[PDB]
Length: 123
Image: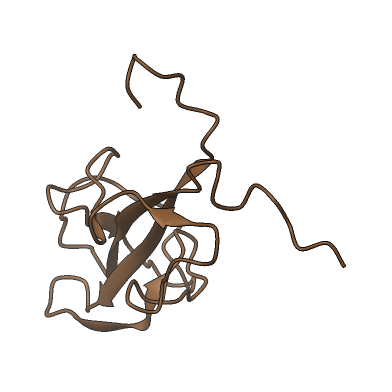
């Protein structure tokens, strides 16, 4: 994303994973039931396990936290699990006591730089 080259032909996608903790509403957090998750809750791989495939180049330096969203300073979103329900279906940018869950997107965008996987193994 610079105004000198037209940043599209590259294929770069922001790779992400929401880490979370769980606590009683107004309590002490422990690792969540599914620590690494998707925004919905689908357990995903962890940033270390998250590696570059043949054809993909990491663009960003490590997994950081995404602050380009309506999220807390450290990325933590307001996931309150009001019974009955299994998951937070609402997220807000403020650490509120009703937080049963909180999660944040660790970000590491990646880029194919177009040329890395440009040709495919023809069989």
